Amino acid sequence: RPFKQRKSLAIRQEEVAGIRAKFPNKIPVVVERYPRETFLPPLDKTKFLVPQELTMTQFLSIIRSRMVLRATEAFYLLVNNKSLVSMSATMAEIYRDYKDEDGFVYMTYASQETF
Image (cartoon, rainbow, N blue to C red; front, side, top):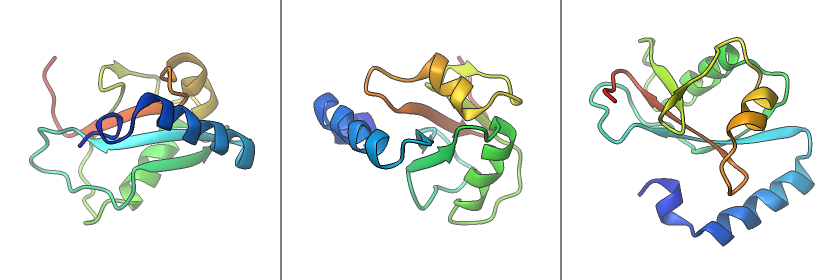
């Protein structure tokens, strides 16, 4: 039920190819709730097409705005569910350094997580 389970690699790469053509100024991000989260609500969508200049800090607020319940609680946003990245980085910086082989960049949100 993670996105990478629901769609094959070739299907995901084809989706990014169309996104890159139609939305060339945007960064394609897949944001998913950490599968073990008990507090924060799910979002009402998975794919965000965000400006290149938007910061991680700003993006947090966009993700919060898409939660099905308006929870104000802090949460972490983990790139590949494993990299805590600079919160002043832009979405183009994060895409350049952390995009998946499929062409999306993946982030998981959690209110707590142990590695």
